Length: 16
Length: 89
Image 1 (cartoon, rainbow over the protein chains, first blue to last red):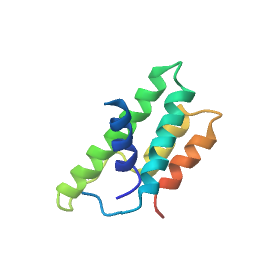
Image 2: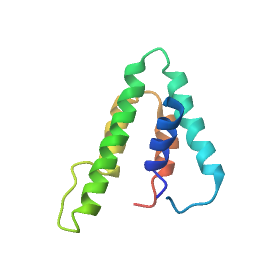
Image 3: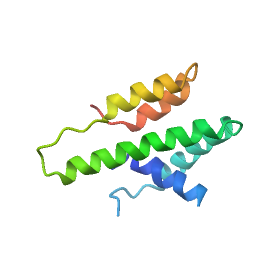
Image 4: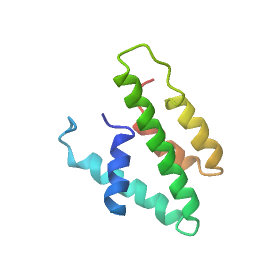
């Protein structure tokens, strides 16, 4: 799955 | 666990999200908004896939495009890069 879940983990990564 | 094995997509993801956070660094409201949108879409998609089959989501790909479009004015560039992630629906 690559469309939304990807951007989700990315943001959660940079954030914390 | 994912399924892909290309570290390129990950890099592109961080670049985009970072681009938005930087472009809207002044207004943290816009950033938090977009995030909440994606989060909601996730809970909806999962609910449907967990409901077995009989279920009607309230937030789909088209619905997200519309909402993000209204919130993102004069910024079709970002909306485009976001739509690219969406498969052939």
